[PDB]
Image (tube, coloured by chain):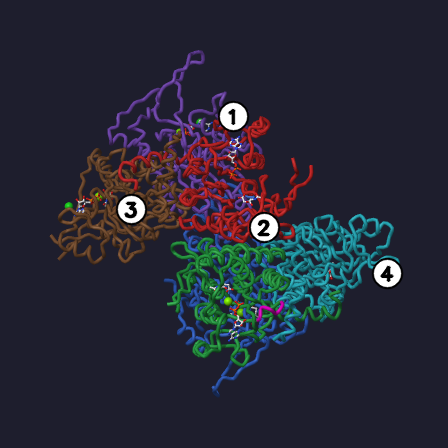
Chain colours: A blue, B cyan, C purple, D green, E red, F brown
Amino acid sequence: TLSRDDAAQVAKVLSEALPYIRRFVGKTLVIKYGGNAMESEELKAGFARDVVLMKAVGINPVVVHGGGPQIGDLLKRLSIESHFIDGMRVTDAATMDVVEMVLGGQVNKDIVNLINRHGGSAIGLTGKDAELIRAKKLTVTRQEMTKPEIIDIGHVGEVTGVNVGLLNMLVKGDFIPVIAPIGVGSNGESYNINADLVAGKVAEALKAEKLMLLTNIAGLMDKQGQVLTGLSTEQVNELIADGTIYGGMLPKIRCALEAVQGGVTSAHIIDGRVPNAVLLEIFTDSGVGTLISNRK
Amino acid sequence: TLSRDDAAQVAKVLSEALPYIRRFVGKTLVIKYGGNAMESEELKAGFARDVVLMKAVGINPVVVHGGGPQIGDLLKRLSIESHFIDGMRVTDAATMDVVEMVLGGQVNKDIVNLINRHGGSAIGLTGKDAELIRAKKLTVTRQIIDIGHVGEVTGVNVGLLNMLVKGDFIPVIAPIGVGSNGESYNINADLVAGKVAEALKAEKLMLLTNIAGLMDKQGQVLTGLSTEQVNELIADGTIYGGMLPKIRCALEAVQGGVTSAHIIDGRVPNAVLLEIFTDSGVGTLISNRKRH
Amino acid sequence: TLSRDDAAQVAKVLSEALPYIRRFVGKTLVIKYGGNAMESEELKAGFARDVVLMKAVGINPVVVHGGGPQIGDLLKRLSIESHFIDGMRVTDAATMDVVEMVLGGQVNKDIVNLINRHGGSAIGLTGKDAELIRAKKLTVTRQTPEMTKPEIIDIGHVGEVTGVNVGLLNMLVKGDFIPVIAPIGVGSNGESYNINADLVAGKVAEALKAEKLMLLTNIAGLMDKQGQVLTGLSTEQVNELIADGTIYGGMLPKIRCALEAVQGGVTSAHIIDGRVPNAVLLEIFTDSGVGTLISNRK
Amino acid sequence: TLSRDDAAQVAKVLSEALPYIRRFVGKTLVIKYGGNAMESEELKAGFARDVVLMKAVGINPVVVHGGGPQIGDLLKRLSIESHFIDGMRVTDAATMDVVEMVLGGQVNKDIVNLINRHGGSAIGLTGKDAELIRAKKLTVTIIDIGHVGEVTGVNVGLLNMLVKGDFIPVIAPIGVGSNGESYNINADLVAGKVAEALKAEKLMLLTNIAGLMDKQGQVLTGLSTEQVNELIADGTIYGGMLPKIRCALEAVQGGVTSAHIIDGRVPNAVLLEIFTDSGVGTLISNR
Amino acid sequence: TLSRDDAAQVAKVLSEALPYIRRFVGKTLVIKYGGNAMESEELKAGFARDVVLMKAVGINPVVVHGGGPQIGDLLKRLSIESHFIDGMRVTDAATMDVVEMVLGGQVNKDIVNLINRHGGSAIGLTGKDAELIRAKKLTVTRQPEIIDIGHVGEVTGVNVGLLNMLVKGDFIPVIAPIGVGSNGESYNINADLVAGKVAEALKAEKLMLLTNIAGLMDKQGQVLTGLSTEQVNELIADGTIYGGMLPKIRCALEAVQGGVTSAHIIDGRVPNAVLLEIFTDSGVGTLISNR
Amino acid sequence: TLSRDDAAQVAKVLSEALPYIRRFVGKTLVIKYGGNAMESEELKAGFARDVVLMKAVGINPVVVHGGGPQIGDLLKRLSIESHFIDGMRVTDAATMDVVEMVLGGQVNKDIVNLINRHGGSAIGLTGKDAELIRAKKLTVTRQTKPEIIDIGHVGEVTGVNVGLLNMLVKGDFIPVIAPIGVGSNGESYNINADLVAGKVAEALKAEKLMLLTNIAGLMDKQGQVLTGLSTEQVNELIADGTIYGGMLPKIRCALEAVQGGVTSAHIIDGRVPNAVLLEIFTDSGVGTLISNRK
Ligand SMILES: Nc1ncnc2c1ncn2[C@@H]1O[C@H](COP(=O)(O)OP(=O)(O)O)[C@@H](O)[C@H]1O
Ligand SMILES: Nc1ncnc2c1ncn2[C@@H]1O[C@H](COP(=O)(O)OP(=O)(O)O)[C@@H](O)[C@H]1O
Ligand SMILES: Nc1ncnc2c1ncn2[C@@H]1O[C@H](COP(=O)(O)OP(=O)(O)O)[C@@H](O)[C@H]1O
Ligand SMILES: Nc1ncnc2c1ncn2[C@@H]1O[C@H](COP(=O)(O)OP(=O)(O)O)[C@@H](O)[C@H]1O
Ligand SMILES: Nc1ncnc2c1ncn2[C@@H]1O[C@H](COP(=O)(O)OP(=O)(O)O)[C@@H](O)[C@H]1O
Ligand SMILES: CC(=O)N[C@@H](CCC(=O)O)C(=O)O
Ligand SMILES: CC(=O)N[C@@H](CCC(=O)O)C(=O)O
Ligand SMILES: CC(=O)N[C@@H](CCC(=O)O)C(=O)O
Ligand SMILES: CC(=O)N[C@@H](CCC(=O)O)C(=O)O
Ligand SMILES: CC(=O)N[C@@H](CCC(=O)O)C(=O)O
Ligand SMILES: [Cl-]
Ligand SMILES: [Cl-]
Ligand SMILES: [Cl-]
Ligand SMILES: [Mg+2]
Ligand SMILES: [Mg+2]
Ligand SMILES: [Mg+2]
Ligand SMILES: [Mg+2]
């Protein structure tokens, strides 16, 4: 329900934002949200609105999300403990059930709903749906008494394929795919995957314009606190070895370097806790957060 | 492999099934899966082959499943106590959250993986996906008693359903529905299959149960039944309580556009297949379909 | 820029307005831009970009433009003999040839270039293209007293639209092109005609059964004789506003348009101040119409 | 009854044959029947039905047929007297007009009438409909074999349109050349070219005997060109089987995944090669 | 060879002719061709060309052919010959096998071959093809004792599905008049009847019936035309019509009442005769329509 | 308005025209309107009508035109001096506005009207319509070390919007293109019409590129007409002074078209009534056919 001094400014901005938007109208966008950036409803609902508005403005967004708080609340209630190694939670059987249930039946459907309340049209999907996300088990590793020591963290996996047929069908039908990071193997078994990595692999598969990674923090930092933009593979590795990039940030650049070298103009790590982080990323070109491009 | 004599078997069956397969090619068949029995183990595999094969034979199956074991479990573990009544779970905010997550994330997906593990391409949806099942607070009178968050479908997104079918996918729908404000609703899986079927004007609505079907005073299966016949059949009362809701549902389906509704014994291996691949209709089948 | 402060606004507002916007995703809105004030380079750019946005947001815009003082400039520079009758310029063959060359070869294409400059795909056409706008000489009579036998005065190549090639416009629209039409019609003999851009705009909206017909003007709505913008008028209210003097001059053909337009298939006709920045965006983001909104039942 | 115990079977076996029926679902299958595998109606009809099946199951058949019976009696009635060399009959004018006439307006349209009685929709065609099979005269040994020619090219567009409009092309082996002259061509070679030209999944050669055999009655499979050519100079391969293999080696050499020579006399024959990986007959793959 | 000046001429008369052509751009025209005198060679190629030309110009032609000089000759070489005389040909199971084999395996495939040689894409079709022309027995009454004329039918259906697919793909359907039963027997039918029933089904613009006479003449032997249905039912009473013209006219009437915009009974001896019909607004022969 | 006896003639004429017409049904011919020369009318109408004919008959004509004379009259009336340097027109900012206005608002639309007067459906466009013709500045020099010579807003085609054309053609509309290109920042360029026509046929991989000129075709030093030449022969011919003046750009634009996907390109005498209709409806060795290896 709008007034003449309202529109005066809606229009002034959409109009002054056309150039930025125009750089994606008709191109596809994969947004990764969640994890620790999900914490408050107002932000959850806020993100939904931004995703729709994009659709409203000609972009075709594709959401991939993590779970964060709820996966842990439930696990608590069930009296199951959780541990992560290098940005991957150790997923034994009982845990894999909770994660598969909470991510695809609660979190996933709840984002689908926020988007739909804001006018959009979402389809909540997971790796099992039409084998959206096929995945062999991920062989993890550690090490300086050396030769590779192979770890076993549980039912954790790695993307081997992605049904773009389904994804493309849904987008072209004007729907906003919202995807949980659970994949299926050759035997129909389940695999818990880091939402980042799924976001990456779906973007590559889809050859999108840009992959947004919304997170818990300004962007990727050096141990000194400063956000570092424009890295290339060699810099990242030096930094990981340095003890700089650790925990859940590991799978994060890993997505970005790959998603870019896999067909994606850009991959931008950003603080999603920031009100309208998404809309801001698109209607503007703020030199905020860690950006990784090859865009010629 | 399939030893020579093996494939010849496989052959004359299809070669005998051509008439039937031909009878329902390119049609919607809303199959309510869920028997307190058909969802145990061995019938799980049979239902998937049945559903896939239907598809491969160019038939359009739309599975609508119930919950049950899976929902009961998690509720116990969370030490949550819920009671029933009219065949419907009283449902407060806390358990509506558990019901929705288990149905939409554990049960729904599993049935989908299953179908897929047998060469199918299933898409698991729930009433929230593109507002696929619109609904409202259902009214429980009890000669008004509040049953909680239980409602009745007020509309179905045929748009999206038609698309999946056209893309040659098998929709597996969880019976949760959304209201005008985005509030969740736990709806009975029969009514849903029933309404989804009305909205698509499906050929058949197939409700799987744990009974031989409907029977009369003498235990006989009462099969070739029509809308008015069933109505009279209830006034007189050969149709007892528990079976009523299921039949009042199958009623509205024929009233609403479905032409042949089958009440089936899901305990029987490959029942859906037998109910199609063989024009018998062993069970209870309501309709206004001309014989000759 | 776009501050957090200023996006917090966009969000809460484009949202509540997403319904409004969305209500036009699907059809055509025929817009008549072109005028006197709005011929400024600043006003045209903004408009060009407004039109592109509308396109981005799923609206199919169809522009009909008029105006330009570069028509008179060229007549003078060419020393084309000027002749008037009853205070109107007689548009003879020499004048019509220049009017056509200017509206179709310069104004038309300049708008087309601005639209393309901001991301749209504009096609510049006149009534000659595939006979987009068929026309016939318009019969004019000198102003006289009521009781006196009217006199037909020949003011030249001035016409009236007898038909529109919707096939052409439907094709272009469907291919994601923004038609940009010059108000020049063709007659049975291939002769040209200069038609009031408002009337052309209105015939084009009717032919396409457009959702909206927007007539941008330079006065911010149809005012009542005391200075107030009026809205949601019906034929009776317009018939008496004219009868008593408040509607006059060029505001006359404009409502006659709207009215006809709406009586002929357009769902709503908006008469707005085209001088206001983002003017056209403003009539689609709120059912709140800044200015006159004619809708015969809505 | 589909009964109890015989349904649990029907299920586990229909299921397990599903992956196999799948390697062909989108792909095209050229089926050459005819020949002397055609001999009885009863049987012949079962073939038609066997075809409608592959079609209800979402497989795309393209039938190429020959003649034996019908081309024999009419050539007999009219006093002609047919002659043969290396699997190909020596066709002169009255012989060509008769072959073109029989194969095209009798044999061909009748199979089409069969496939239609069992549900599917078939269009009877010859190399002349839209110049479907283009041809020059065959270069062989000089042997005035007469009006026998080769396949210059196939109207694949006509075929792809029909197939995807849901029809079954039934193709008589008659070819046409630049000037519009008929040429009689072996139904085998036609099928092999119509398969190469469509890049079909597999070429099915239904014959009279089960698989190309050696002088000892021993069936062979997986034969490569070097050895097969030893088998022709030898005496081992002769008559009708001469064009049969060569059309098979070519189809593989040029596009078709595989090509299988089986016993068309066996009821449900075709189905068996699909619903299984039988291992019987003479299958030609590519290594 | 349009030399110099002629170029100047054709440009003028082609333009005139364009609007007449436009009428029929996009339209379907079912044409009945097969006959007696028409069976000249020189003249057959002219029809093939005319049809390709119609295709180039934007019109979609559908060809229905009859003609059996080619049958009598095979029957003969096989010493089976019989008598028929009453519009239709009394077909025993034997003559039928031959009728169906020469009609759809020789005659038909040749009209296809010609059109093809001239730049067309023709498809030879009989009623057996996808049950293109569904049929049944017949009931011929002696002028009521029934005269046995089975293996001869009444058209009871037309797969328009197929014809549409062929047209849309820019093919020229060429259909031999053989009907197929609900069981699969062939019945031998009359071209004009097939053509008209094929016209009705496609709701064509025109049914063109190539005869061997300038059109429907009257008492004084003057060409008739541009009249209506009720009008034509009239002159039948006048008893003006006779022979194999009677049904040719009943073919059209129905066709017209059956949706078809207009029917033309024209002399198919005249070269480019069919084109004369689409180029001149009027109709150069006898034109039945009633809109 | 119909004839009868000459309905029979149209029949006989198109009947025999089929072998040739058939060659191009469904193919697009990029025709550059020229030889217009004396601004006749029986000749401008003749062309318009030949183009509609080709369309009726199933051919897909695309037209490209110039307008030197017309630009010249206007510049003259506005008292703006005119200058040509090596065939291209020196185009300062003021000349560009006049060039663009006349070619796209007058000459262009007038051919459209003519084609429509004869039955066609023509669309008049310039490079600025949906960036139909993308261009950049052309670099010109001279050997009075060459020196760069600024001759104004004269560009060279950098790209064509086939999307728009294909759509137009498929809708049974005949595109009429004025040779004005657009730059990166929206500047307007004035391009040789032969060159634009060449780039368009290339982009469209056209069956034929027809250049109607005012002469007969490419000729010897003795006035004879050369036909079906190779890219190697055209070089020896320009190399000895056989080809010069405006004929140079013409042929160079013709080879390019062929070395870029156009089947055949011909230089034709556009002064001959129905010049178009004859290079199709018949087959004469009249003109200069350039096909490389065909
Ligand atoms: N170099 C680094 N720069 C920034 N954050 C880092 C870095 N190394 C590790 N991190 C960790 O990554 C976290 C965000 O990743 P994560 O916990 O996986 O959540 P999510 O993927 O759900 O957004 C930060 O809260 C921080 O503790
Ligand atoms: N009731 C009225 N309300 C508003 N404007 C009116 C009214 N009656 C007449 N006008 C005149 O209409 C003019 C605007 O339209 P028009 O005459 O077509 O000129 P322009 O080309 O500047 O738009 C106003 O400048 C005003 O003088
Ligand atoms: N080496 C061989 N192995 C098997 N069959 C052979 C061989 N050489 C010749 N044949 C003959 O080839 C026949 C099949 O080919 P052909 O006579 O042309 O009939 P069809 O056209 O029905 O295939 C068999 O019936 C058999 O008599
Ligand atoms: N009123 C009539 N007007 C014109 N021709 C007629 C009329 N009545 C009968 N006919 C005869 O009908 C003939 C055409 O029918 P028919 O002899 O059966 O041959 P076909 O079917 O081979 O064209 C004309 O050649 C003419 O002799
Ligand atoms: N070998 C040549 N063959 C043909 N024309 C030539 C030759 N050398 C030069 N010309 C000149 O090129 C002219 C054609 O090009 P041009 O003057 O640009 O005119 P247009 O392209 O407008 O018809 C001919 O009229 C002729 O005077
Ligand atoms: C394997 C794995 O670590 N998975 C993630 C998936 C959710 C996410 O990325 O937030 C996890 O927390 O369990
Ligand atoms: C309301 C209600 O009873 N819901 C059902 C839905 C699942 C079903 O039918 O199995 C329930 O168990 O909670
Ligand atoms: C040339 C030639 O041999 N033709 C084969 C065609 C039929 C077939 O292969 O069965 C023939 O017997 O006449
Ligand atoms: C029954 C009947 O009319 N038969 C015709 C069919 C051929 C035709 O009309 O040309 C016949 O000669 O046998
Ligand atoms: C640059 C240039 O040559 N311009 C030409 C364009 C006209 C044409 O090609 O006909 C000119 O006179 O201005
Ligand atoms: Cl840190
Ligand atoms: Cl005022
Ligand atoms: Cl010279
Ligand atoms: Mg993480
Ligand atoms: Mg005014
Ligand atoms: Mg053989
Ligand atoms: Mg020149």
**Label 3 sits on what residue type?**
Asp
Q: What SS does tag 3 mark?
A: loop
Front position among marks 2 and 3:
2
Q: Is mark 2 within 8 Å of ligand 9?
A: no
Residue C168 drawn at (x, y percent): 43, 40
Q: Chain of mark 1?
A: E
Same chain letter for marks 3 and 1: no
Q: Amino acid at mark 4?
A: Gly
SS label for mark 1 = loop
**Element on which disc 4 rests:** loop
**Which marked residue is nearer to the observer: mark 4 or mark 2?**
2
Which residues lie in the magenta part? D263-267
Q: State the residue position of label 2.
A: E96
Classify 10 Å Cα crowding around label 2: few (below 14), some (14-19), many (20 and above): many
Q: How far apart in space, not on screen, are marks 4 and 2 (Cα)?
A: 60 Å
The crowd level at tag 1 (other Cα within 10 Å; few <14, some 14-19, many 20+) is: few
Quadrant (top left, top right, bottom left, bottom right) of the C terminus of chain F: bottom left
How far apart are the alpha carbons under marks 2 and 3? Answer: 49 Å
Residue E175 placement (x, y as % from top left): 52, 47
C1 and B40: which is toward the camera: B40
Q: Are marks 2 and 1 on the same chain?
A: yes
* Within-10-Å neighbours for mark 3: few <14, some 14–19, many 20+: few
Q: What mark, if any, has residue E219 been given in the picture?
A: 1
